[PDB]
Image (cartoon, rainbow, N blue to C red; front, side, top):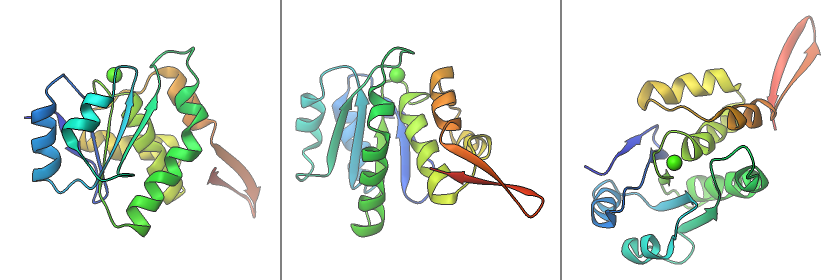
Length: 161
Ligand SMILES: [Ca+2]
């Protein structure tokens, strides 16, 4: 009963509540190949308990605070990590924070926005249909800020950067 949800064939989103054994049980039972930890707490115990091979556990220290830019600062690196684990190494990814509703959900939504070239509201509803998420307002503006709307042939086409 570790609280994480399958979002699509490639991604899980969840939290962390201090029971690494439950988390390890979820990861191993569900064949999760890679874990991204987006937390402001100590990650070494999670890394140790999961014991994944070198390179299959990534940590970015980041807060959920209109003041911390660390998730935004690392969005490109995080995206490329997911893309290479999913497409080149064929792994599923657990993205987690503490509650699994804002930090982790923000990266999952962005991965779906950019791989599908769809806007925030479309990706958010897709994810929210599988797990009730609620990105903080500044993460919503971050993700919306990645979308460009360009005029062509009497339409506005969205591009996700
Ligand atoms: Ca949290």
